[PDB]
Image (cartoon, rainbow, N blue to C red):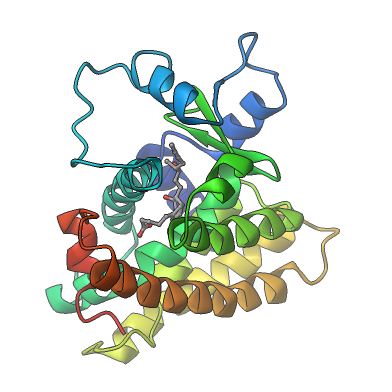
Length: 269
Ligand SMILES: CC#CC[C@@H](C)[C@H](O)/C=C/[C@@H]1[C@H]2C/C(=C/CCCC(=O)O)C[C@H]2C[C@H]1O
C-alpha cells in the first residue's frame, strides 16, 4: 500500500526493463546458476574468441573500424552503455508523472542522469576481479581493462573503483530500482525549466526509498543517508567523465563515438 506499493511498482518496472539484474549477476558469479562458468575475456585472443560465438555470436561485429586493442574494447564499452541508456529511458516512462513533464525536461533529466544510474548499476555485475558482459555469458577481467593504454584505462578505472566500493552497501534490485529513479529525478541538472515539478516527483521517490530501505534493511541504520551521499560521488564521477569524453573527442579523433553518446556529451557541463 502507498509507499509500499510505490516501491513495488518501481521495482516491477525495473525488472521489466533490465534483464541483467544484480540477483542474476551474483547467481552467476558465485557459480550457483551456472555449471558452466562465463567465458573469460582477459586478452586479445580471448576477446577474439568471445566475439566469434562464445560471448557475442555474430559473423560481423557491427563495431566501427579500429586499429588497436584499446579502441576496440572502448567500442565494446560504448555498446554496453548505449544498451543501458536505452533501458533507462524506457524505465523512466514508468516513473509516475515523469512523462508529463516538459519534453525538454525529460530530455535534460535523462541526458544528465543516465550515466549516474549506469555507474550505480555497474556495481551489480562487478567483483573486484572483473565484470560480467552479454547477460553473463562473458566475464572481462579488471586486469585486462587496466592494461589498455591511456586514456582508455584511465576512463574505466574510476567507475570500476566506485562500483566495487558501492557493493559494500549490500543493496539489492528492489533498492536499486528506487535509487536510480531518485537519480534521474534530480532537480539540479543544468537547464531544467520547471525545477519545482521535478523536485516534487523526486520527493515521492525519496520518501519511498527511505521507506523501502528501512523495510528491506532493518539492521542497516544509516543506509539512507549513505545512499544519498553516493549521489554526490556519482555527480563527481560523471562530471569527470564529461571531461574525459571531451578529451577523447579532441585527442583520439580516430576513435568513433556512438551518436547517441555524442548527443549526450553535447554541451554537457
Ligand atoms: C571487451 C569488454 C568489455 C567491458 C565492457 C564491454 C563493459 O561491458 C562496459 C562497462 C562500462 C564501463 C566502462 C565505461 C566506459 C565509458 C565509455 C562509454 C560511456 O560513456 O559510458 C563506462 C562504464 C559503464 C559501463 O557501461
